[PDB]
Image: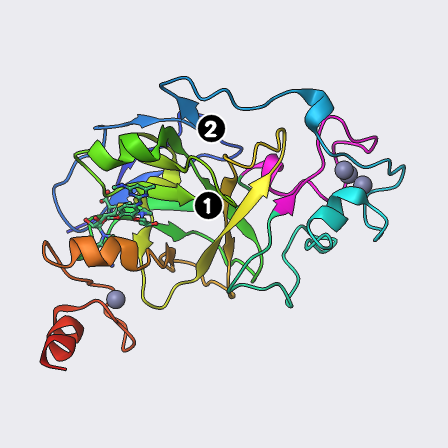
Amino acid sequence: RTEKIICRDVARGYENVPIPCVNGVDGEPCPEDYKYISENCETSTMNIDRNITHLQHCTCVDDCSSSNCLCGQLSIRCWYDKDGRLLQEFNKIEPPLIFECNQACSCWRNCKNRVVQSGIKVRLQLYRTAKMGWGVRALQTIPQGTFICEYVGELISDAEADVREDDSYLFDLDNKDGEVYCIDARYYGNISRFINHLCDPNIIPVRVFMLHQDLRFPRIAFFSSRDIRTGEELGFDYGDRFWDIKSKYFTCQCGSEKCKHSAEAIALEQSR
Ligand SMILES: CNc1cc(C)nc(Nc2ccc(OC)c(OC[C@H](O)CN3CCC3)c2)n1
Ligand SMILES: C[S@@+](CC[C@H](N)C(=O)[O-])C[C@H]1O[C@@H](n2cnc3c(N)ncnc32)[C@H](O)[C@@H]1O
Ligand SMILES: [Zn+2]
Ligand SMILES: [Zn+2]
Ligand SMILES: [Zn+2]
Ligand SMILES: [Zn+2]
């Protein structure tokens, strides 16, 4: 049973790098029951505030590496090192909101505070897992704090999320208050839609603002939470909102010693 290259690039050239699909496990064809999009899309009236006069922006004439950069200060500080990687001290538990530089800023497009807006740089692969369907793995080593990819899909309201038949591809956009919105990657999504849950995760979501600062719509950036080895499967914690609903349909197959959502773990808690 050989590992076969089934698609040279599921992103159809929309990313900085190709994202190939292989399958060495079963007869599943390349997934095509969805539309690959590299950036979030709208299917109803959202009115994202794109007023350029509403952007907070810096007056930096350097590379935005100084603590005097307004955009960094909105983020508490800029959290990216000279190489575009999150600082070791970054709060991976309760990440702060990141405000990247933007088109109102006086700085250049290559300033130090533009990691997420610059897109995917690591080589990834869509591959058939043993027990969890499709998954995404690294084709190279990835240091801690590296930007991996964005959780991209269809923006929907809370009310629309409430009636979506498939709730498997939802991501909540947390905001101080208000109407609350979700990304649904079921019908429209990028590579992130294929990232599985791991009880021992190696990536974390961070809310980021770039070309707009409409707080209803943070963009969701995945960064590595530790060093990742070539071939390693990417995964994040889907959280209890997911597992509270899904546990009765199926159980976690992440296979970790720490697995908290396996059949075994659920039964042990049922039993108390
Ligand atoms: C069903 N109505 C709503 C409404 C709002 C505002 N938010 C949600 N969130 C939600 C519902 C179900 C979910 O999984 C079963 C869920 O999972 C979130 C979790 O991040 C996992 N997704 C899978 C890819 C990321 C979120 N649902
Ligand atoms: C966002 S999709 C991830 C991509 C999915 N594996 C696929 O093939 O399209 C989430 C769904 O993948 C599966 N999945 C993800 N993480 C899992 C896990 N730890 N154990 C079992 N199934 C998992 C479940 O069917 C889940 O509802
Ligand atoms: Zn600046
Ligand atoms: Zn800048
Ligand atoms: Zn700036
Ligand atoms: Zn698990």
The image position of residue 139, as x and y in percent, is 43, 51
From the viewer's side, name the closer residue of 80 and 104: 104
Identity of the residue drawn at 19% across and 63% down: 253
Q: Which region of the structure is painted magenta?
A: 98-119
From the viewer's side, name the closer residue of 206 and 120: 206
> Under tag 2, what secondary structure?
loop
Three-letter amino acid code at the position of disc 2: Glu
Ligand 6 quadrant?
Answer: bottom left
Instruction: Note whether 219 is above or below 137 in the view shown.
Output: above
Q: CA distance from mark 2 to mark 1?
A: 19 Å
- Pair 2/1: label in front: 1
Q: Is residue 186 visible?
A: no
From the viewer's side, name the closer residue of 252 and 158: 158
- Residue located beneath label 1 in the image: 174
The image position of residue 134, as x and y in percent, is 24, 46
Of callouts 2 and 1, which one flags the residue occurring earlier in the amino acid sequence? Answer: 2
Say whether residue 24 is left or right of residue 90: left
